[PDB]
Image (cartoon, coloured by chain):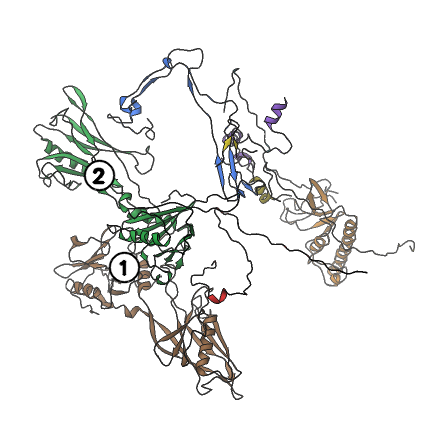
Chain colours: A orange, B blue, C red, D yellow, E green, F purple, G cyan, H brown
């Protein structure tokens, strides 16, 4: 089903990144999401967001240029920037170096998205 | 009544082979009187000689070439006969316009 | 002549000294037969001593 | 991993051959007439190539936080 | 139409003989070209878009080179002499229904299983002479067969008097009893008709038949009524429609293989055969051998066609031109 | 038929006559094999 | 070619072939965990 | 060739003229019929599958009737006579590059925004005369334009010897300067040529052109080297490709509008115009006005074509048969 998976040689190999597609947005779905997990009980994801190590990269946000020149993102969205940091590791999911290269880059966009959340909350509450 | 092979017409209409009366089986015989002789083992030899392509089997590239032209011929052949053990157990009645 | 020539090749183009070069070897689409060939080359040696 | 275009190539292929060692026919009932992708038995040339490419990687010197190693 | 070929067949129309390639001016010209060493024969023919040659005939590799007259490709439209069988009754028996059945066999489809049955009918009366009978049945056979509203022309039907006995008076759906004014009619002639012909799409094919009679009682016996004998044919269709179809097929060997498939987008080939004239055929059939252990023959044929004017002058000039340049014993027909 | 009837089909088009056209092909065009790891039948019959 | 024998037997031709069938690979997120 | 109609326009081929309705025997015959009271006019013509009539021309409701000869429909091929500009220098100056640019304008595509520019180049010598210039110039224009490996011919290049002064010296790509032995040349004539023609699919059109010059430096002044004037035309395209396209269009008003489209499943109409002959055209424009409130006219026209050989013997007989039958005043050309 091609979403972050390498289905080759009869086997199903993942790099850890979960391309949660086919559902729709939160407001278009009956359930309001894909309900990937009940672990907060309504853990609800939409068609654009991707997941690495139970951390959700949102597709609704944008990439400010102050955290584009630092943390070195490539896409227009945080979901599209996590969809470009995994491009090397999606074809070599058993590689020791690529699973180190993927875990190091996903923590950067984790710290890039968390900085965007606190700077937004300071803007709205201020 | 097949008019493709039967070409002589009868004077009363239709083909001349329609007016032929055949009693194939007179009584019982305890063995088949009329049977189709076929050789045991002689399946018809489907046989192709060809050149660089074979349009029937669909083979592109030939290791063993018969010749050098873009051709593929079929050759098939069958050895076959029939046998009527008792032709006195079978009475026919032929119109004479078929001329025997 | 092959290339659609219906007027002919001039007599100046068929003289002594004119080099000729292979392009290719066309056949039909249907009932084709064999044409063409393949050319090779040989090396020569040199010499020194002690 | 095969696409349905690639199954259509597998499907249209030789799968029957014919008699083999104008043809003169000899031997009576057992008549005998007298890098390529199929095998004249209905097989496919699976050529598989394995090779060692070159990959650009980085050796990175970092410091442990708790001890200066 | 589609013909059978011995691996190829290509046709050239011999509208002129110009004796050299510098005199080829109009379309359809022909020179038979050969050299002094009689080893190659070819035909520089002027096409409507330039000069074109044939494959080069090796004169050690010819198999037959036979030229046919235009009288040998004419289909003779067969006739039948329908009369009264004098053994049953010389006169029409005055109470019986006299019915004749025509059994057609190629109908609208080729096989002899596609058939078509038409009938003519006359009630015979007292005092009706045999000439008054054939005047009454050729009209009733024309009203069913020579009608205006049938799909295809089936037969042509005439009457023959006993005085002239050579000329045929045509009977159609419009001919009345007063138009055929003669008292010595002795047969009814049923002749085939040429079917419609379309270039390349509808070949020249005919509809055969057999005039079959029905049984009419005489002294209690149900004796077959008449006799039909195949008299020699006197009308032939010309060679105009076979050679017009023959240029349409063999132009696809030297040219485009499809003819109109998609019509904003075709290569319109100009054809040279008038379909309204008779034509002679010359077939030089040959092959191509090599010099190996794989040697033998790729068989070919070249058809040349010249116009026939009655004494075959335009064809015999081509044979007289091939015989000097190539040195073959093609029989001047 | 030309070859073995088309196998790349949906399951509903594998009707009663599609299976019979497959089996009639085995009746006719399955006698001559260039077997790659077997001997001929006439060779084996001589051995027995 | 020949349906019978001269011992009154019947020619039984068993054919076995590997046809192709269309299957679907579905990737389903389980509601409990996420696996 | 899709032409414009006011309303419908019917074309009838007059290959032969008869005087009686029972005289029509060949495909192409026509008779002009009318009443004895001169209240209607119509043409009974012989189609190849029956006799056809035209519409009934009310002889009170004719608008105009004019007959056009063959020379009025002949396209005169324009010529450009290129000479060296006399005020610049009548002889070529030594060491300058003489370039001529031929500016085409409807190269493919009707708009003039589709253009095409072909070039000719000559560098002059110290001993080059004016007659030696045009020899080297037209050998370079026919080198760029009339190469055999091109798609289509565009223009024709002609030299002029002043000793003959009316006979063209044609220069092609196969000519050398060894063939041009004349030492008295005064101009180069560039003349446009006949484009190809496929009936219905490709109309008869032409590519216009105008030669332009580049500047040369004779005395420190960058002056253009030549002048190109248009002389009177001497070669004309015949009328055959215009009338065959005129019958092909107007055989969809009588016949079928689906020409050839679904190729085996069509009807083909047979065309009685030979495109290798010149023709004369007769146009009778008229209309239909009904009884009471349908007074709007349906302004329609009927075209007749008749082949002429020099003196128009067939069209002046076609005009002469109509005016004694209808009562018109059609001009005898």
Quadrant the C terminus of chain H occupies: bottom left
Viewer can see residue H167:
yes
Asked if the residues shown at circle 1 and circle 2 are in contact, with their CB atoms under 8 angstroms apart, the answer is: no
**Percent x, y for residue H53?**
22, 55
Q: Crowding at label 1, few (<14), some or many (≥20) Cα neighbours within 10 Å?
A: many
Picture disc at residue F47: none
Quadrant the N terminus of chain H occupies: bottom left
Tell me the CA gap for discs 1 and 2: 45 Å
- Residue situated in front as seen by the camera: A92 or H231: H231
Using the rendered image, report if marks 1 and 2 lie on a common chain.
no
Q: Secondary structure at mark 2?
A: loop
**Percent x, y for residue H280?**
26, 65
Viewer can see residue H291:
no
**Percent x, y for residue E86?**
14, 26
- Residue situated in front as seen by the camera: H125 or A56: H125
* Chain letter of the residue beneath label 1 in the structure image: H
* Chain letter of the residue beneath label 2 in the structure image: E
Residue that numbered label 2 is attached to: E233
Q: Secondary structure at mark 1?
A: strand
- Residue situated in front as seen by the camera: E58 or A93: E58
Q: Crowding at label 2, few (<14), some or many (≥20) Cα neighbours within 10 Å?
A: some
Say which quarter of the image contains residue E3.
top left
Look at 39% across and 71% down and name the residue there: H192
Residue that numbered label 1 is attached to: H10
- Residue situated in front as seen by the camera: H137 or H304: H137
Toward the bottom, the furthest residue is H219
**Percent x, y for residue E113?**
33, 32
């Amino acid at each position: 089903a091609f979403g972050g998976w390498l289905n080759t040689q009869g086997g199903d190999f993942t790099n850890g990144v979960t391309f949660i597609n086919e559902g729709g947005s939160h407001e278009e779905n009956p359930y309001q999401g894909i309900q990937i997990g009940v672990d907060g009980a309504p853990n609800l994801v939409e068609q654009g967001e991707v997941v690495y190590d139970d951390y959700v990269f949102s597709d609704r946000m944008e990439i400010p240029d102050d955290i584009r020149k630092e943390y070195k993102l490539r896409g227009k969205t945080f979901a599209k920037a996590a969809k470009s940091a995994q491009r090397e590791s999606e074809e070599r999911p058993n590689d020791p170096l690529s699973t180190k290269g993927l875990q190091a880059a996903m923590e950067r966009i984790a710290t890039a998205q968390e900085e965007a959340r606190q700077r937004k909350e300071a803007h709205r509450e201020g | 009544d097949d008019p493709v092979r039967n070409k002589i017409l009868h004077p009363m209409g239709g083909v001349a082979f329609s007016y032929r009366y055949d009693i194939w089986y007179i009584g019982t015989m305890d063995q088949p009187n009329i049977f189709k002789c076929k050789i045991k083992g002689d399946n018809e030899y489907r046989g192709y000689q060809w050149g660089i392509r074979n349009p029937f089997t669909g083979q592109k590239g030939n290791p063993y070439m018969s010749f050098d032209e873009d051709s593929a011929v079929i050759h098939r052949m069958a050895t076959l006969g029939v046998c009527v053990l008792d032709p006195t157990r079978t009475m026919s009645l032929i119109p004479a316009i078929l001329q025997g | 002549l092959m290339g659609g020539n219906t007027q002919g090749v001039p007599a100046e183009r068929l003289q002594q000294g004119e080099r000729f070069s292979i392009e290719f070897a066309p056949v039909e689409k249907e009932l084709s037969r064999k044409v063409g060939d393949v050319r090779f080359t040989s090396p020569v040696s040199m010499r020194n001593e002690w | 991993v095969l696409s349905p275009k690639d199954i259509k190539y597998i499907e249209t292929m030789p799968d029957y051959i014919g008699q083999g060692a104008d043809e003169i026919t000899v031997r009576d009932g057992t008549y005998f007439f007298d890098l390529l992708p199929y095998d004249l038995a209905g097989n496919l040339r699976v050529l598989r190539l394995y090779w060692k490419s070159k990959r650009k990687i980085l050796k990175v010197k970092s410091y442990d936080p708790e001890t200066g190693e | 139409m589609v013909i059978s070929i011995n691996q190829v067949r290509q046709l050239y129309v011999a509208k002129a003989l110009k004796a050299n390639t510098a005199a080829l001016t109009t379309a359809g010209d022909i020179v038979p070209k050969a050299d002094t060493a009689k080893t190659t024969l070819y035909f520089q023919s002027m096409s409507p878009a330039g000069i074109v040659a044939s494959d080069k005939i090796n004169l050690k590799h010819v198999l037959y080179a036979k030229a046919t007259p235009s009288e040998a490709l004419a289909h003779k439209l067969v006739r039948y002499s329908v009369t009264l069988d004098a053994d049953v009754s010389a006169t029409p028996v005055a109470g019986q229904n006299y019915i004749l059945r025509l059994a057609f066999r190629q109908y609208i489809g080729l096989s002899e299983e596609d058939q078509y049955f038409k009938y003519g009918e006359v009630i015979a009366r007292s005092g009706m002479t045999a000439s008054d009978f054939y005047k009454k049945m050729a009209i009733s056979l024309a009203k069913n067969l020579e009608n205006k509203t049938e799909s295809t022309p089936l037969v042509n039907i005439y009457l023959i008097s006993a005085a002239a006995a050579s000329t045929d008076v045509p009977v159609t759906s419009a001919t009345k009893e007063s138009d055929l004014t003669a008292t010595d009619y002795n047969q009814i002639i049923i002749e085939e008709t040429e079917q419609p012909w379309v270039l390349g799409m509808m070949p020249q094919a005919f509809i055969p038949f057999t005039p079959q009679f029905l049984t009419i009682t005489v002294d209690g016996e149900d004796r077959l009524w008449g006799v039909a004998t195949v008299v020699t044919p006197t009308k032939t269709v010309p060679d105009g429609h076979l050679i017009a179809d023959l240029e349409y097929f063999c132009m696809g060997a030297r040219g485009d293989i499809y003819r109109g498939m998609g019509y904003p987008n075709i290569i319109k080939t100009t054809y040279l055969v008038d379909p309204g004239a008779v034509y002679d055929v010359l077939d030089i059939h040959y092959f191509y051998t090599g010099s190996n252990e794989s040697v033998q023959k790729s068989e070919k044929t070249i058809t040349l066609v010249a116009v026939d004017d009655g004494s075959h002058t335009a064809m015999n000039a081509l044979i007289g031109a091939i015989n000097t340049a190539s040195g073959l014993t093609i029989a001047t027909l | 038929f030309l070859n073995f009837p088309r196998q790349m089909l949906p399951f509903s088009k594998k009707t009663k006559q599609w299976r019979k056209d497959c089996l009639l092909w085995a009746n006719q065009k399955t006698f001559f094999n260039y077997s790659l790891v077997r001997k001929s039948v006439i060779h084996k019959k001589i051995n027995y």
